[PDB]
Image 1 (cartoon, one colour):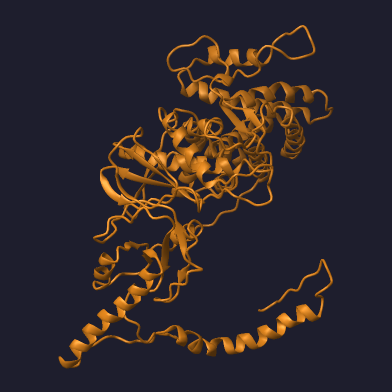
Image 2 (spheres, helix red, strand yellow):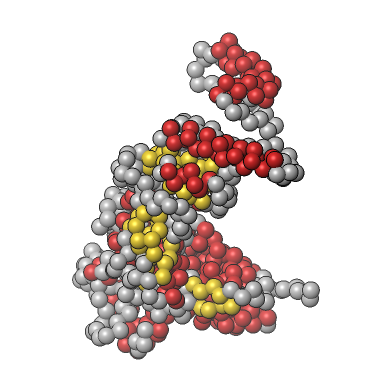
Amino acid sequence: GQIIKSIAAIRELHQMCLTSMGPCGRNKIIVNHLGKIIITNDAATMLRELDIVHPAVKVLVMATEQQKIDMGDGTNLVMILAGELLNVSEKLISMGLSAVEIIQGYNMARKFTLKELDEMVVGEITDKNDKNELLKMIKPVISSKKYGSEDILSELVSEAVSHVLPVAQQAGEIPYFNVDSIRVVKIMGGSLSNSTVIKGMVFNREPEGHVKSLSEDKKHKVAVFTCPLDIANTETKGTVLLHNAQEMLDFSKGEEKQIDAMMKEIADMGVECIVAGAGVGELALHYLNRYGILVLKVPSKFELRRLCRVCGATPLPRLGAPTPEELGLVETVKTMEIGGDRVTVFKQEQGEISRTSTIILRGATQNNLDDIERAIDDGVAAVKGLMKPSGGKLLPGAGATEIELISRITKYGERTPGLLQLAIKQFAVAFEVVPRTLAETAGLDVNEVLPNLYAAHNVTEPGAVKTDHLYKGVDIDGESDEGVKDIREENIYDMLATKKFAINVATEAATTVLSIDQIIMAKK
Amino acid sequence: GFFYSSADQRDKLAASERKFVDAKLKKIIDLKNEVCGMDPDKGFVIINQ
């Protein structure tokens, strides 16, 4: 009976994910063996930081990572739903039903569910990319993660998305929004109300020079130099040495006139910013102070990729060749104090629209600072789901989707004759874990809210056309309430691309576990 | 490496690297004009391992 104990091993980790989805969710502190503490609310990220013993657990972990890579949202919906399909299948094992027909029953029920998703679409997203229109998609993403920040972070995330998107409509051929266009930075001090939206990358380091910021001139030229600043010598070896004191005056003054000659030609071309990926010498910073050139050092090669897509600069393998064709152009750059420390940021005005933006976060809490950093990344992939593959269609969330499917699946159960009726009935009951989890973790009584959810989607109407309100979902309460409330008041919806993709992944996840009747292991 | 100290020395030092490149490149671009130049809806692909 190891197939029964295999579900119990997942059941131990099932209750861990039941405390994740919903507003009651909380991050888990994990101390790595290297002395580094990683804290995140996302359950998919935690799976990489946990040591897996039983190999059957990795099956659900691999399916969970698929939800984060493609759609980026719904990782908690895949793991929780896949864990419940094993519990409803455990009763069929004790009943005597073979696991072969159980797998065949899910394949027939999956095709019936996908055909009903097109009829459950309420609204359609016009892809206007307006600041007020993006508030409906971003609100449920921030919801059920961090409480109280949903109102403040709604305007910060929606504003940064509209900056990187150009003006276009009804065109899906050329992609625009990427996953790297939104970067999250953190700084000690401040609050969430004082946070602003930047149209470009934000640098929290020091300029390392006497020039704090450039002027207001239009189209500042920015050059990226991968070669370090130093006198040109032989690429092979070429170490500067002093044999006698006579050559000291020639070598010292030789490097001063050589560097100044290269900086003079760059300043004549109109380049007010020099990006040096490598170290900068001592004599190089002295000449850049009089010419008024901002000093910037970016040793990380990952940040230079998003910089070339904004101003248009190109990295030069050599030094002293300011080719005007490969130079970048930025409208305005300024150095201001944000969060208590003076830093040099990167923004724009009108032309040279940036394809990458960065949101500055401020707060007095260290634990909640890294939690919002991981929460915004989940909202970045939500914009990617607005493309042609069912980006405009949406379904009502807050547990209203799983409850509404109960009436439609049970209607097709008696319609299909044969032994498949056992798997179809258990397939709809497995959706009851979503409303029960939100009601149990919120302190609400099961004998109260749960029977009201069944009566919300099932009523007696003297007519063929549906009426009254089908939008009533699961309410978290927390203060007081009578019955349930309409979800359309808070405008909490779920995209079709996220819900439809989570069904096929969760179906194949539980299919693999039920299909394995034997597991062979060996000690290392 | 080839490091030039003046604009005139840029094409002189780099001429050794582009000597073999320009020899083959100028002969390939002439094939597109002589052959398959007028024919619409066609293309020319180079493998270049």
